[PDB]
Image (cartoon, helix red, strand yellow):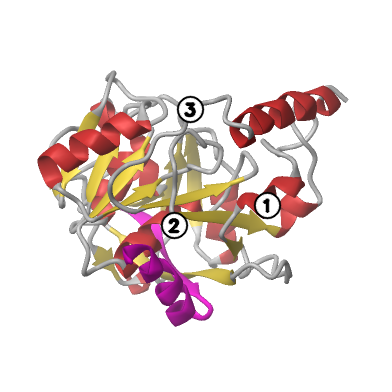
Amino acid sequence: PFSYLYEKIINFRNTLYDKGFLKIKKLPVPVISVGNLSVGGSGKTSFVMYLADLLKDKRVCILSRGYKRKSKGTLIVSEYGNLKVSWEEAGDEPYLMAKLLPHVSVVASEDRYKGGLLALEKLSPEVFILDDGFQHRKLHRDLNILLLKKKDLKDRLLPAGNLREPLKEIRRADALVLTYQEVEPFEFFTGKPTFKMFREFCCLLNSDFEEVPFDILKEREVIAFSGLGDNGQFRKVLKNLGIKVKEFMSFPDHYDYSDFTPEEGEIYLTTPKDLIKLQGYENVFALNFKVKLEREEKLKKLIYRIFY
């Protein structure tokens, strides 16, 4: 019920943009924005990566904001897979994406347009992917992709609910991706190109972010841990997968793992974002979920239209 007035402020902000009262800038190569409406688990990350993969015959650069990083200012995190900074400096997300996408460039920058210019100067990418870019209207995108999970529809605005913008804002989108289909499937019809996203369990990632068979977990029990607070969602996934934990450690959300002291011979499971902090530790893994999108080729055709 402060959500009523938050709605009024956001609306105003959107009207300023609609009526040309707030400046909008444009990069000289196509921009694809991936975003959502809600705070909380989104699949944005999974989908940004999937989308980068689809562009495998294009020089791709991801524009990410970083969130909490040990540095300040526009920063090239990775040059087509060549990592230039540590995860501390990069921020968890952009680093994780740099690690998993060896063909792609990643830039961390609060000033997104500026990040874009720096990339062009130094990397000459053919396409930008604007990570979490739906509300960032000051940067023009040629393809505005909006992610929606079933929960979003039954949700409210902040501070009551998790919505950053009202549901009506869905109409700004060029295309919709309906997430978490594997667990909470739903349909949605707007006339907009619309795609169903599934995530399914492939295998493990070792600390080198190479793929390792889920098989090694058999008749083994693991020690599981994580930080960034998200400490039962993980427990939930592990349970659903029939994975036998034998203790669950929960570290503070900043935890840098410098004094992490493993038990010899024991198998550890943690999250992809914790794992980036434990490069080199063997017998430490994260779960690897792949994205399958329905009508991938349609999606591909839609994306490739930005190149004309």
Q: Residue at x 33, y 66 (%)?
A: 308
In the displayed structure, does residue 235 sit left or right of residue 253? right
Q: Are marks 1 and 3 in contact (CB under 8 Å)?
A: no
Residue shown at 31%/47% (left/top)?
62
The stretch of residues the image draws in magenta is: 285-308
Q: Which amino acid does label 2 sit on?
A: Ser
Q: In the rendering, which numbered label is found on residue 59?
A: none
Mark 3 lies on residue: 23
Q: Earlier in the sequence, mark 1 or mark 3?
A: 3
Residue 280 makes an appearance in the image: yes
**Residue 10 in picture, x, y percent from top left:** 70, 29
Q: Distance between the residues labelled 1 and 3?
A: 22 Å
> In this figure, which residue is indicated by the disc labeled 1?
170
Amino acid type, callout 3: Lys
* Magenta span contains residue 283: no
**Quarter of the figure with residue 51:** bottom left
Give the residue number, with chain letter if any, for mark 2. 46
Structural crowding at the residue carrying mark 1, measured as other residues with C-alpha within 10 Å and reported as few (<14), some (14–19) or many (≥20)? many
Is 307 positioned to the left or the right of 222 in the image? left
Residue at x-position 78% and y-position 30%: 7
Q: Which secondary structure, mark 3?
A: loop
Up the image or down, 264 lies above or below 53; here it is above
Secondary structure of residue under mark 1: helix
Amino acid at pointer 1: Ile
Percent of width and height locating residue 230: 55, 39
